Length: 230
Length: 230
Image (tube, rainbow over all chains, first blue to last red; front, side, top):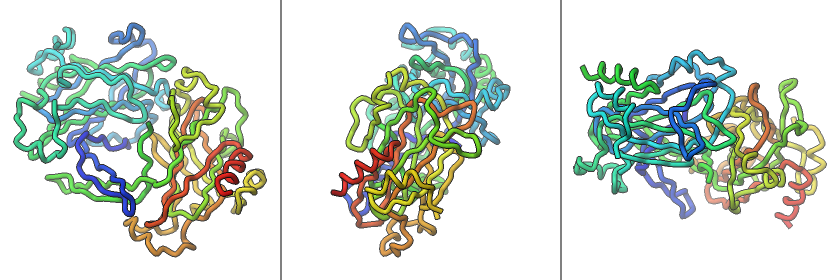
C-alpha cells in the first residue's frame, strides 16, 4: 500500500549507535483516509492558479476540532488491489482502465488548503460555491510537494512533544468545518489521470479519532456529512 | 532534498499512545550516494530484460564488505539546483532542460541487482563487459518498486536488532565488488527522462562507512574507483 502518513510531531529521537546523529520518529496521523481518484481527459479545471495553471478541488469535511491535518498527493497510482478499511475509491477511478491508471502525468503538486463557509453538513454544497473564508486552518499553501512530501495544517505554536498537547487551550485547535484542497502542477506536467490524496487527522492525546469525509463533488460530500450526523 | 534512505533494520519500536500498535523506525543507511541521471529520447537500451523489456544499467562499486545495500529509484526529479557531496549528477542530467527534467515518464521500476567479476577497481571496465557472476549479493530482483520503495540486498539471515550484527561472521557479509543495477518498467510507462538512483550501504556496528561509487559508464566508474583508493 501507501507509505505511512506522518504528522509533524516527533514521537521519539534515537541516536544512531556509535555516531552522534539522532533520527526522529514521527507520530503518524491517527485518522487517515486515502482518496483514490481520476481526473478525466477533457475535465474542465475547477479554477486557475498562478494565472496559467489548471487547479482541481477536493473537499474535506472535518467533523471535530483537531491538532493537525496532513495532505499528501501521490500520482499516478496504477492498479491498487482490494481497497483497505480507510480507502475511498471514486467512480471515475473504478471506471478507468489499468493502462489509464498506470500512465504518469505530473510529479510536483502545488497544494492549497482553504477553509470554506460551512458550519454544518447541510451548508456544504452552498459553501463550496462561495468564496473561501478570509492561521493554517484558514489558508495554507505549499507550492512544491514531490517525492511523497506533505502539506500540513498546523496549530500556531505547536509544542515539541505530542503529549504536551494535553490541556492545550482548545481555542488553539483547528476548527471543525469544510476545507477545500486545490491541487495543480507546473508545465510540462498536467493534472490528469489517477492519483491518491491521503488526508490525515491528528487529535490531542486521549481523544478518539473521527475520520474525515472526502469528495470531489460537494453535493455528494454534503449528502455524506448529513447522513453522518443525523 | 530527497527522503531519508532507510535500511531494513529496526532502530526503535515506539508504542502509539492508547493503542496496541507500534511504529517501527528504521535505521538509515550510513553511507548514501544519490545519482541524478537522464535517459535521452530514443536512447538505445543497455540491455534486454524479461525477453524484450528495455533495460538500463547503473554500475556500483562497493569498496568494503557490508551488512546491506539499498537501491531506490525515483523519477522524474525536476530541477535540483546545487548538488551536495552525497550527490552525483551525470552529464546527460546536466545538459537536460528544466522542462526536460520535469516531464514524468514511468512510475513502477523493475529492478535487478547482479554482482560482476571485478575484485579491484582497475578491473571494473573489463568486468562490466563480461557476463554477471552466477545469495542477494550475487543476484536479486524486485519486479515492482513504486511510491519510492526500495530494492534491498541483504545477508542470508539478518537479525532484527542492528546491534546483533556485532561479531557477525564476516563470511556472511555481502562482498566488496562491482554490482550492476538493471532498471526497466511496464507499458504504458517507459524509461526516459530524469531519475535519481539512491544507493545506500549499511556497515555492521562500529565500522565507519565508505561511500559507494556509482555511474552508468563503467569506464568512468573505474576511473573514480581507482582514484578513491589510491
